Length: 9
Image 1 (cartoon, helix red, strand yellow):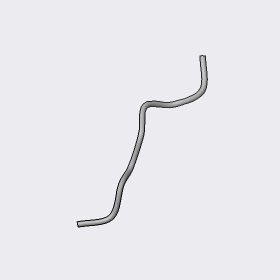
Image 2 (image 1 turned 180 degrees about the vertical axis):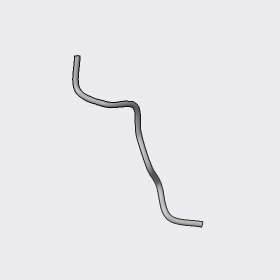
Image 3 (image 1 turned 60 degrees about the horizontal axis):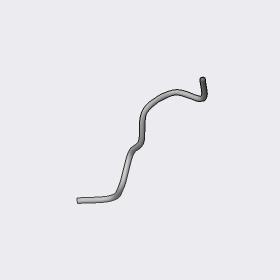
Image 4 (image 1 turned 45 degrees about the horizontal axis):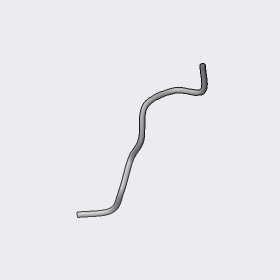
């Protein structure tokens, strides 16, 4: 799985 992170701010 690729790393998807929380939306900016």
